[PDB]
Amino acid sequence: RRRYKVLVAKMGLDGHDRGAKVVARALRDAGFEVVYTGLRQTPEQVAMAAVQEDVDVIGVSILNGAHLHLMKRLMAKLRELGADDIPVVLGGTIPIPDLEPLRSLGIREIFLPGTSLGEIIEKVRKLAEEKRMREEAEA
């Protein structure tokens, strides 16, 4: 309870991901509780972390890799764990022909290089607010 809680996770190619840290720190400065290891993770590790830390929003940063196959695996494992209501957002350089397929998996927002930090915070806020409302809207 208290502050909205966000998991920020790196997935994909093990290269240098500068973006992910900056998002994590911007979310913290905007008053969210942020889980961020700094380390590349597999889709199952993300999904488990997410449910173990009982987060409000999952933010994934893929600098490069096979976005659709990774996000398909993450989405499946969340669903397995009964956590499919947790909203997931994705950042990276995603080719335009992949944007719709990714949204079809149920990713709520895709943050491209041109998306401002301010926009990120606002959408993550909105999604976490919704997520709590939907939870708290069940007895």
Image (cartoon, helix red, strand yellow):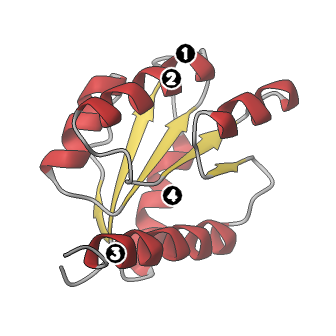
Q: Secondary structure at mark 4?
A: helix
Q: Secondary structure at mark 3?
A: helix
The kind of residue tagged 1 is His
For label 4, the crowd category at 10 Å Cα-Cα, with few meaning under 14, some 14 to 19 and many 20 or more, is: few
Q: Nearer the viewer, mark 4 or mark 3?
A: 3
Residue with the mark numbered 4: 22
Marks 2 and 1 sit apart, C-alpha to C-alpha, by: 5 Å
Residue with the mark numbered 3: 132
Q: Secondary structure at mark 1?
A: helix
Question: Of the residues under marks 4 and 3, which one precedes in the sequence?
Answer: 4
The kind of residue tagged 2 is Lys
Residue in the image at 57% along x and 42% along y: 106
Query: Is residue 122 among what the camera can see?
Result: yes
Residue in the image at 75% along x and 59% along y: 115
Q: Position of residue 123 (x, y in %)?
A: 60, 69
Q: Nearer the viewer, mark 3 or mark 1?
A: 3
Disc 1, disc 4: CB below 8 Å? no
Marks 3 and 1 sit apart, C-alpha to C-alpha, by: 28 Å
Residue closest to the eye, 9 or 98: 98
Marks 1 and 4 sit apart, C-alpha to C-alpha, by: 25 Å
Residue closest to the eye, 2 or 135: 135
Q: Position of residue 4 (x, y in %)?
A: 32, 75
Residue with the mark numbered 1: 69
In the depicted structure, whether residue 85 falls above or below residue 63:
below
In the depicted structure, whether residue 133 falls above or below residue 6:
below
Disc 2, disc 1: CB below 8 Å? yes
Q: How many marks can you see?
A: 4
Marks 4 and 3 sit apart, C-alpha to C-alpha, by: 25 Å
Q: Is residue 108 left or right of residue 60?
A: right
Residue with the mark numbered 2: 72
For label 3, the crowd category at 10 Å Cα-Cα, with few meaning under 14, some 14 to 19 and many 20 or more, is: some
